[PDB]
Amino acid sequence: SGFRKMAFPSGKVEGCMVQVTCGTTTLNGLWLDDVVYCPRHVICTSEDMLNPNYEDLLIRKSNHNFLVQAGNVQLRVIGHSMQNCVLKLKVDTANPKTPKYKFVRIQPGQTFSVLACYNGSPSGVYQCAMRPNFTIKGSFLNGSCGSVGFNIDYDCVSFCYMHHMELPTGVHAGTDLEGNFYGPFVDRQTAQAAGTDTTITVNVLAWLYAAVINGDRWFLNRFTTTLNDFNLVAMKYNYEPLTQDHVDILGPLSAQTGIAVLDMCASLKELLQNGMNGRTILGSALLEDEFTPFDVVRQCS
Ligand SMILES: *CC(=O)N1CCN(c2ccc(Cl)c(Cl)c2)[C@H](C(=O)NCc2cccs2)C1
């Protein structure tokens, strides 16, 4: 029993974190086999923060301009290339701590763990979600660029996020490990703003199913709804639309508990209307939306 925001064990990722320095700029890099991945704006200068020409800046660098330190060890860079917004640095040494890994691009609503790092050293691990507006609500200070987000399923680390920047609202933007941004953001310091954010409805429903599984029933009601009528209500609360994929995806938790998906949607409609009147659900007085249907199945059963 019990229900916690649970991150993945971070040890496989810790063994991959290094420090990358170009010029006066230092940030974190990800050392997998003989390649170090890091945000390409490490090669920017103060003057070049608004409209960097990364192709121009990179053609002017030689390998010896890049200082890579794994612990006390300086790694020798033997090549450099750019892939979208990520720099790939070839090193003379393959990382002996390289886990089984893959790079994955995730979709909004997906969760992952973040290993926040500074100067190549881990500071902490926490659980995050890709918001519908393609930002993440992280905990990042300056120098944390290059920290990565990941899931571990079996013994394989799936890297899905690299941190590049903080926007003016204090939310964070980054890329997948192929260097493509999530969302419409760019690695420039020009004015950028996140779209309006919404609540991840399928994750809320998944968490209410987890609550029923942990014996919490006070928010259930005798009603059901249509998918269409529910979405008309939810949009009015800045909840995301619920699709039939979402309904299919909750199928298992619906089976496990006896409550149809559209019955639980009726309970969510009512909670949006009344709030919790002092009560809590699985320990929260707000509706939690950073647990996926998949997370709920692995922590409860
Ligand atoms: C994450 C980190 O370690 N930071 C280093 C500086 N930085 C950036 C440098 C260059 C560029 Cl092109 C970008 Cl987008 C970010 C990070 C950051 O969030 N900069 C602050 C910004 C000011 C205006 C827009 S982003 C922090």
Image: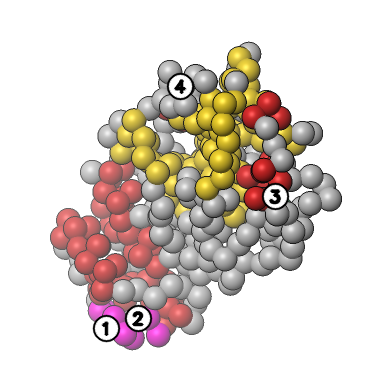
Q: Residue at x 74, y 62 (%)?
A: 190
Which label sits in the foreground, 3 or 1?
A: 3
Look at the magenta stretch and give its main secondary structure. helix
Label 4 Cα neighbours within 10 Å, binned few <14 / some 14-19 / many ≥20: some
Q: Which amino acid type is marked by label 3?
A: Asp
Tell me the tag on residue 56. 3
In 3D space, how far apart are the residues under numbered discs 3 and 1 (Cα atoms)? 56 Å
Cβ atoms under marks 2 and 1 closer than 8 Å: yes
Q: Which amino acid type is marked by label 2?
A: Phe
Residue that badge 2 annotates = 230
Circle 4 SS class: loop
Where residue 92 appears, x then y in whole percent? 52, 20
Considering only order in the chain, which callout, 2 or 3, is on the residue closer to the N terminus? 3
Tell me the tag on residue 94. 4
Q: Which residues are magenta?
A: 223-232
Q: Is residue 28 visible?
A: yes
Circle 1 SS class: loop
Considering only order in the chain, which callout, 1 or 4, is on the residue closer to the N terminus? 4
Q: Which amino acid type is marked by label 1?
A: Thr
Q: Residue at x 57, y 26 (%)?
A: 78
Q: Quadrant of residue 205?
A: bottom left
Question: Which quarter of the image is occupied by the C terminus?
Answer: top left
Residue that badge 1 annotates = 226
Where residue 297 appears, x then y in whole percent? 26, 48
Q: Which amino acid type is marked by label 4?
A: Ala
Cβ atoms under marks 4 and 3 closer than 8 Å: no
Cβ atoms under marks 3 and 2 closer than 8 Å: no
Where residue 216 appears, x then y in whole percent? 32, 56
- Work out whether residue 32 or residue 300 is closer to the camera in this orientation and state it: 32
In 3D space, how far apart are the residues under numbered discs 3 and 2 (Cα atoms)? 52 Å
Is residue 230 located in the magenta-colored stretch of the structure?
yes
